[PDB]
Length: 408
Image (cartoon, rainbow, N blue to C red; front, top):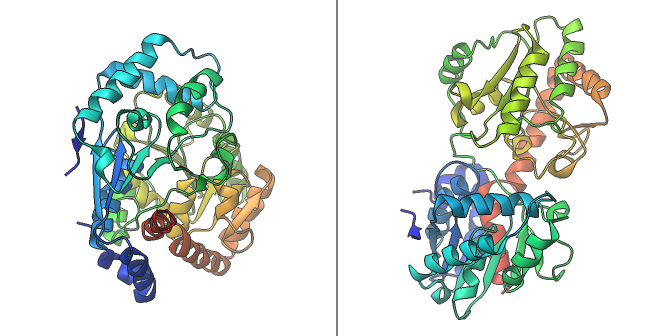
């Protein structure tokens, strides 16, 4: 039941990246002019990958590459199975792979493969596990790349042994960061490509001051008082309780300080909602702390407003992937205080773009320092934006793809 998904042009980013960068990109694109580059995944809706593809595809076409995008479809059971796969591959050991599951998985993949001859494109890229087995139903005549968005450092063995038979047939395995790659795979075929942000999406586009204020008021956020923020999915290893504590320490000296705990989570995330509830219990009736989620109307655009209005942003994760929330904050010129883990450690240049702290106590002095030194804050912020502009925006993401395709 596979379907292809139905305006972004490199020109739209010229003002952001400069003519030089634009030429460099067009240069690399030249060598691939006319070639078909197709993407395959499981959804054209929501944020994350889908959101990026909605801009990346038209963006590639603007530089002359026949980029197309297809989404596989399947019964709800297929996704319950792939949901199980996702968790198992990321480490959950209590899950079991049954023959019924393998079959359903392979059959759904077999079905989707009938809709279009993916093997006829010059370059085929498959995102994540759900459609990895598509490479199995064609006569491979060109390069097939596997884009992995999850953590495969220590997978439930039986699920990985099953999936690797398909994955091993790809010419490249593209991971977010080192800590997520599966070390068993051929070293020269495994490649690192961090996720990126699209400066023009709802989450990152620069909002007008009137809109930001209209959003802050709607959520009872006072822009005239200090604001510290952490946007993250509610989970136990995100330092949410540490941030609450940091906020309380800071409040002893800056009584008007407000804390924004922002998070968007699927309804299919009980553990997340359970933690969300425990956070509200911990906070109690201190309403200077705002818990902002999609349960109560928070979406991309308001998350955008919350980050812009923040004086300081934190990311006290104990566990973290690349950490795009840090990328978003840095793009908005905000100094970020975080723990040196995953992409947080990679993105923050301590003392330059933000600060890497070890515990809550350090975090406290740094937010107080930043609150006291707005000039240092602006400085670090500008440098933080510059680092994102040169490394983690969608056009650099697209350029990384060109480099890969060209190396084939």
